[PDB]
Image (cartoon, rainbow, N blue to C red):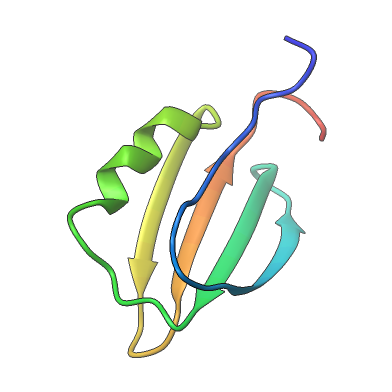
Length: 69
């Protein structure tokens, strides 16, 4: 209730975090990562929900929110 913690364990990482609105979202981009089946352990950290993808970079994690953070 005080705060939800999202933990990503790996060798890296360079990251960037930013916000989006309509709907309110928090987005993290991780570099030096290729998307993998372990991405599902990500379900632990939603966020109304969490979606993850990649575009020949660079993985993007998107957290829809239930309240301003």
